[PDB]
Image (cartoon, rainbow over all chains, first blue to last red; front, top):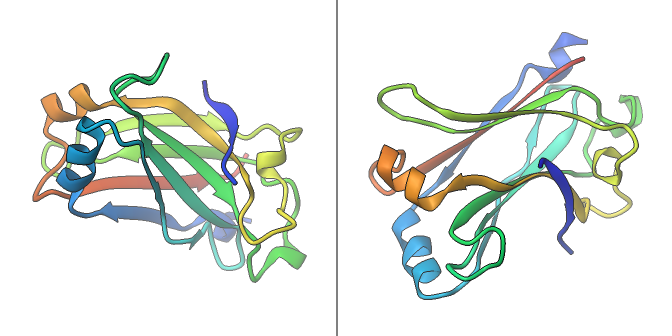
Length: 8
Length: 155
């Protein structure tokens, strides 16, 4: 945290 | 150069109570901001904000906030990956006691490359950015508007 996340 | 980071974006999220009432009913909320440039020339970015449901494991009732790169008009003349310090805030419109997270870029993450589509599917930010109970207790929402600010500064 923070982090990378995926949002298609 | 400094002019490549001179921009500051304030996302005005109107009718916030509407999203809150839906979140209280167990609906995930996801909002996508208008694009903005860190500068001219500069990087095109956008924001993604979540309200997590009351039952989401590990992050129930949080605002989540992520930055995404986009294909921008100046991309051919920019260094890649995007490198710098990103400051994300929920603004206190009266007392100035903003809720601010500061994060440095990581050059090995897909989120900071130029995407091969208009908007990078990979974003970077905070799952637990600000809890809804903390937002309520502080009164950040004024006239049903939440203000979310994004500033990028160079290394």
